[PDB]
Image (cartoon, rainbow, N blue to C red):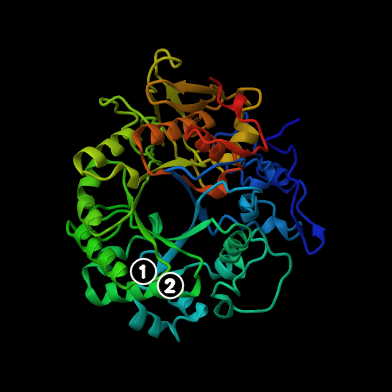
């Protein structure tokens, strides 16, 4: 009996039927997923297995909690009938955020807008998408006249869908017809429904992200491309007046990121672009944020000073994915602290924050730090710490190809954690897994002696401590990567770390912190 999870996929009512009761468990059966044994499987667990438990808190202090909401998280072909069970989607309902009497986030960040001409991401540089959205007359025109212009790269998910976007029936209309605020369905229509329920909620577009930063370096160097880019912002902000913020998540100026063109002049060029956007005087655009790596060497390479000199008002510090497979050592993925000589957990929020404030003279209040709705794992792992309960995490792994995850190898998402890996209500691990608190990092991890799988994750305890860090250090606030993953437990912990008075109580968080 649980206030956090369901014991069986409750399904989803669509067109007066519910075709996906138990769908999550049918997938598990088809794939032979067993939590206490599987080291090398995907779960495909839908967020439907979690109960929705966002509290709300007074949020009118000097901090803000932001939410990256991904436009692919709505999908799950299991919803429609009984045909597909060997794979699935996240099925993340935008309506989990529709709380009474407040909001779990001040600002929802649509993730992600792509760029016309981006041939790293798209074989045709998104040209067919431009045509479908009605911003180009044919694919040649898209590239010839609109290179550098932003558009959502998933028009179904952005402006057409019903399921998990707050709508209850299919209606005729193409993407071109619906690519504006009042006609949108999809996630942008879902954002509008939340806008209509809550006038204080803010909306940001994030352009780029890890897979879509391939075109930034080229755009920022070029006055005609910068001009197309600014036009892209004006167009989107005219089509969707409810938007008021822009996150240009170029990952990262001056360094390699996912394998992008890059140049030492990227940050200086990016600063020209941000000024050019400011100069357009888009009446509803109140603020521009950018992304920063947590690696001080990559921070140096980004020329953060140039960007702040051009009037950037926020830095979303991408404090997650610190554990990357490849070097045979375990690591925390989103930890606040580390010992300076640590070769396992090589990065930390604190190292990065200190670097920005002390070396780059960034205003602390501009900085937002991340908490994560997902994990970074390695199978075939060995914990080598001498006293795990008192000492910093150390450990190694051999072959971690095809490690346990939810939708992609090596990454479990939050629903899987609370349903099959950790029992926060009983205060202990599930299915042969044990939770360890690393007091040096102030981060928790999960590990099973039986499966030999190591799982680095955020918990209520660490997210609360991140909220505490933000407050102590006077930072801007926190963001979740990504908010569609959270059932509310993570975000509750953030608000509590900020010392916020509760307004609407759905769940008592007290027993979930475990000291």
* Res 407 seen here: no
- Report the residue at 43% width, 31% height from top: 468
Q: Which residue lies furthest to the right in this view?
A: 16
Tell me where residue 271 appears, x and y as whole percent. 23, 61
The answer to whether 467 is drawn above or below residue 452 in the figure is below
The answer to whether 270 is drawn above or below residue 358 in the figure is below
Indicate the quadrant containing the N terminus: top left, top right, bottom left or bottom right. top right
Tell me where residue 467 appears, x and y as whole percent. 45, 35
* Res 368 seen here: yes
The answer to whether 453 is drawn above or below residue 88 in the figure is above
Q: Residue furthest left?
A: 264
Identify the mark nearer the N-term, 1 or 2: 1
Q: What element carries label 2?
A: loop
- Horizontal side of 271 relative to 395 (left or right) equals left
Q: Which mark is residue 93?
A: none
- Report the residue at 30% width, 24% height from top: 339
Mark 1 → mark 2, Cα distance in angstroms: 7 Å
Q: Nearer the viewer, residue 236 or 264?
A: 236
Q: What element carries label 1?
A: loop
- Report the residue at 29% width, 38% height from top: 352
Residue under pointer 2 = 126
Q: Nearer the viewer, residue 47 or 270?
A: 270
Tell me where residue 363 appears, x and y as whole percent. 28, 45
Residue under pointer 1 = 118
Image marks 1 and 2: residues in contact by CB distance under 8 Å: yes
Which corner quadrant of the image does residue 393 belong to?
top left
Q: Which residue lies furthest to the front in this view?
A: 60
Tell me where residue 225 appears, x and y as whole percent. 28, 74
């Amino acid at each position: 009996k649980s206030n956090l999870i369901y014991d069986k996929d409750p399904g989803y009512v669509w067109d007066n039927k519910n075709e996906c009761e138990g769908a999550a468990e049918e997938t598990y059966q088809e794939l032979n997923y067993e939590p206490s044994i599987s080291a090398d499987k995907l779960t495909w667990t839908p967020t439907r297995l979690a109960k929705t438990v966002f509290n709300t808190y007074e949020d009118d202090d000097d901090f803000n909690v932001l939410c990256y909401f991904t436009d692919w998280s709505q999908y799950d072909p299991r919803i429609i009938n009984k045909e597909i069970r060997d794979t699935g989607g996240r099925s993340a309902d935008i309506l989990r955020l529709n709380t009474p009497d407040g909001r779990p986030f001040k600002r929802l960040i649509y993730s992600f807008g792509g760029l016309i001409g981006d041939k790293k991401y798209s074989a045709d540089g998104n040209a067919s998408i431009a045509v479908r959205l009605g911003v180009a007359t044919d694919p040649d025109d898209a590239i010839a006249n609109h290179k550098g212009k932003t558009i959502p790269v998933d028009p179904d998910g952005a402006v057409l869908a019903s399921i998990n976007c707050g709508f209850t029936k299919w209606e005729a209309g193409d993407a071109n017809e619906r690519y504006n605020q009042e006609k949108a369905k999809g996630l942008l229509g879902g954002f509008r429904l939340l806008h209509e329920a809550d006038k204080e909620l803010e909306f940001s577009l994030s352009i780029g992200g890890w897979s879509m930063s391939g075109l930034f370096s080229e755009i920022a160097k070029d006055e005609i491309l910068r001009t197309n880019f600014v036009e892209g912002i004006k167009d989107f902000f005219q089509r969707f007046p409810m938007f008021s913020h822009l996150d240009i998540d170029w990952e990262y100026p001056g360094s390699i990121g996912a394998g992008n063109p890059n140049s030492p002049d990227d940050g200086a060029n990016f600063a020209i672009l941000i000024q050019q956007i400011t100069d357009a005087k888009i009446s509803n655009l109140k603020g521009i944020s950018i992304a920063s790596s947590a690696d001080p060497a990559k921070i140096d390479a980004a020329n953060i000073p140039a960007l702040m000199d051009a009037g950037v008002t926020g830095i979303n510090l991408m404090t997650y994915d610190f554990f990357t497979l490849g070097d045979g050592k375990l690591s925390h993925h989103t930890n606040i602290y580390r010992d300076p000589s640590d070769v396992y957990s090589k990065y930390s929020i604190d190292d990065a924050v200190t670097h920005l404030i002390d070396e780059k003279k960034v205003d602390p209040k501009a900085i937002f730090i991340g908490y994560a709705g997902y994990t970074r794992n390695a199978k075939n792992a060995t914990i080598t710490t001498s006293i795990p309960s008192e000492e910093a995490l150390k450990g190694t792994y051999t072959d971690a190809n095809q490690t346990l995850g939810s939708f992609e190898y090596s990454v479990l998402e939050w629903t899987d954690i609370i349903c099959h890996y950790m029992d926060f209500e009983k205060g202990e691990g599930r299915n042969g897994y044990k939770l360890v608190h690393d007091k040096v990092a102030k981060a928790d991890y999960l590990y099973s002696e039986a499966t030999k799988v190591f799982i680095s994750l955020d918990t209520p305890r660490s997210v609360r401590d991140k909220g505490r860090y933000v407050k102590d250090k006077g930072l801007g606030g926190l963001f979740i990567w990504s908010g569609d993953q959270d059932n509310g437990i993570l975000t509750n912990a953030a608000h509590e770390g900020l010392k916020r008075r509760i307004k609407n109580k759905v769940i008592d968080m007290t027993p979930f912190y475990l000291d």
